[PDB]
Amino acid sequence: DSDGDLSAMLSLKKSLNPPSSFGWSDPDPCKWTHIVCTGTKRVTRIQIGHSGLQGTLSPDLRNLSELERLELQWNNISGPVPSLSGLASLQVLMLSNNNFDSIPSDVFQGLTSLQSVEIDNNPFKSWEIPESLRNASALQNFSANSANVSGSLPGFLGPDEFPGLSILHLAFNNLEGELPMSLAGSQVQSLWLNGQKLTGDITVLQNMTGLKEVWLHSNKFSGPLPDFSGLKELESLSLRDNSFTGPVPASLLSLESLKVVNLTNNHLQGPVPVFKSSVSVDLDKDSNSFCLSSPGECDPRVKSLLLIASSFDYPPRLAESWKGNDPCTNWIGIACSNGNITVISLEKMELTGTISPEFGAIKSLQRIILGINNLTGMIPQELTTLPNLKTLDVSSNKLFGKVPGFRSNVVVNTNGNPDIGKDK
Ligand SMILES: *[C@@H]1O[C@H](CO[C@@H]2O[C@@H](C)[C@@H](O)[C@@H](O)[C@@H]2O)[C@@H](O[C@@H]2O[C@H](CO)[C@@H](O[C@@H]3O[C@H](CO)[C@@H](O)[C@H](O[C@H]4O[C@H](CO)[C@@H](O)[C@H](O)[C@@H]4O)[C@@H]3O)[C@H](O)[C@H]2NC(C)=O)[C@H](O)[C@H]1NC(C)=O
Ligand SMILES: *[C@@H]1O[C@H](CO)[C@@H](O[C@@H]2O[C@H](CO)[C@@H](O)[C@H](O)[C@H]2NC(C)=O)[C@H](O)[C@H]1NC(C)=O
């Protein structure tokens, strides 16, 4: 009630200790500068950003039951952020750019009206995004850049609990682990996750069709680029300084909405991408694994090997090795005679995926050695059309199906494939 608000405001004045000329002098805090109250003397707004404040924040803040907007940003307030639990009308919370040293796990408990949270640039002790946030079903904006956020990106941030989430900014924290698949379906429009140690692939982006701005640079993301054709509002895509593999997808190259793309410093393969003239492209020379230094089709041998790599799920070691346009110099697993590929030898490379029928297109092949990997599927019939093939070793994989009929002088070894001959 109004007496409770009066007491809480007096406690806040004491903790913050504002200057004598700040205007918190009247016996009725509803008459104080930068405070808004209802006609029945309930506090609804406290708006004292950029006010040079130096104290701490009283825990009695949580007693202001009708508080809607709390702005304390760009001061020098220290100590812990008090629990705000129970402030069911709090709609806007701005604490960015202060000196807060911690934020508690129950801080968002029962904050059902919360729409916008900004707590960037505070020297918080390490903390994880808390479960208490899950009651903010109308949450639209959550910003906590440079706030020492740790752990994984929690899956509860998906549309199942945050159907209105629009801005999620968590740059320059300590996040690790992979993107949770529960983000699928999210209507987030601006996503900042740059500048930490996130890993895994970014396939979940395919299911986030409201994205306009995606900043994932400076992480440890890997794997090939996903299908972008569904992201018809995507304007700004920053993927630089990661470990992405595979080619730049045509689905991205033809995306009409695209305005800015950053691809520098990855392990992207295939031909150099050509974007529309209107797109600002950040792609430093020699900062990926493209076959040429400028746009143009790759060498025929390279094209074949890249199809083979694709079927092997773009092996990370090959993405970093198979650079340039000459497979006969310094490529993992590749030997040549007079420029013709004679050996593809990738034993013990933890390969996944399947054996591409494109092996059959490399007519100079003498040895295909793929033993001790995690390959599945069948041995393609196309391999029997290799007239110089001497040895096919596919030992110790997870292959199945009938072995096609090879010439009677081809050495074939399927040792250690328990399902060879079985159908699946
Ligand atoms: C957070 O919000 C949940 C509901 O949202 C769901 O969980 C969130 C964490 C998040 O995942 C959301 O996306 C998701 O939709 C609230 O949960 C509801 O809480 C109320 C009570 O607080 C429950 O109401 C009770 O229902 C009982 C039957 O299931 C019923 O027996 C109870 O009646 C008894 O109590 C009432 C008074 O409360 C009394 O009037 C009755 O006479 C009787 O004794 C009562 O109605 C809902 O079942 C919960 N689930 C819903 C609504 O889906 C949760 O409270 C909230 N928590 C915080 C901290 O804000
Ligand atoms: C992503 O690339 C864009 C386009 O190159 C970068 O934006 C440009 O930044 C330069 C500064 O280096 C500005 O002077 C240009 O005006 C910007 N162009 C824009 C915004 O269209 C952007 O900085 C890159 N992002 C990262 C994280 O490196």
Image (cartoon, helix red, strand yellow):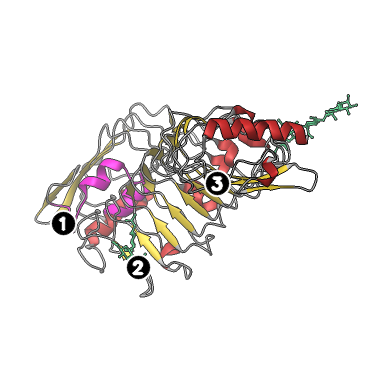
Q: Report the disc number at residue 48.
A: 3
Distance between mark 2 and mark 3 Cα atoms: 39 Å
**Hey, what amino acid is under mark 1?**
Asp
In terms of image quarters, where does ligand 1 lie? top right
| Residue behind mark 1 | 326
Q: Residues within 10 Å of mark 1 (few under 14, many from 20)?
A: some
Q: Residue furthest left?
A: 338
Does residue 182 appear left or right of residue 5 in this picture?
left
Q: Residue furthest bottom?
A: 277
**Hey, what amino acid is under mark 3?**
Ile
| Residue behind mark 2 | 280
Does residue 320 appear left or right of residue 101 in this picture?
left
**Hey, what amino acid is under mark 2?**
Ser
Magenta-colored span: 305-328
Residue 406 position by quadrant: top left
Mark sitting earlier along the chain (1/3): 3
Q: Residue at x 36, y 39 (%)?
A: 196
